[PDB]
Image: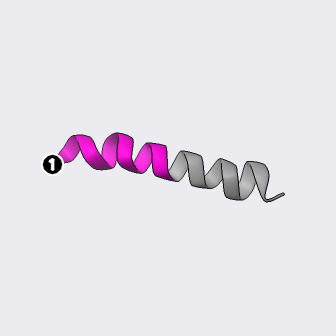
Amino acid sequence: GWGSFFKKAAHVGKHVGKAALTHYL
């Protein structure tokens, strides 16, 4: 569905970007 990527990607890109960028560094 579309809702997925919306939060799925926002939550995935956000949790990953923060955990990999806002955290890894």
Residue type (three-letter) at the residue carrying disc 1? Gly
Q: Is residue 5 above or below residue 7?
A: below
Q: Quadrant of the C terminus?
A: bottom right
Q: Position of residue 24 (x, y in %)?
A: 78, 59
Q: Position of residue 4 (x, y in %)?
A: 27, 46
Which image quadrant for residue 7? top left
Structure colour scheme: one colour
11 magenta-colored: yes
**Residue that lies at the very extreme toward the left in this rendered image:** 1
> Seen in the image, is 4 located left or right of residue 14?
left
Which image quadrant for residue 16? bottom right
> Seen in the image, is 15 located left or right of residue 9?
right
Instruction: Tell me which residue sits at (73%, 55%) in the image.
Output: 21
Q: Position of residue 19 (x, y in %)?
A: 68, 52
Instruction: Tell me which residue sits at (51%, 52%) in the image.
Output: 13
Which image quadrant for residue 6? top left
The secondary structure that dominates the magenta segment is helix
Instruction: Tell me which residue sits at (62%, 53%) in the image.
Output: 17
The residue carrying pointer 1 sits among few (fewer than 14), some (14 to 19) or many (20 or more) residues within 10 Å by Cα, namely few
15 magenta-colored: no
**Range drawn in magenta:** 1-12
Q: Position of residue 3 (x, y in %)?
A: 24, 40
What residue is shown with label 1?
Answer: 1
> Seen in the image, is 5 located left or right of residue 18?
left
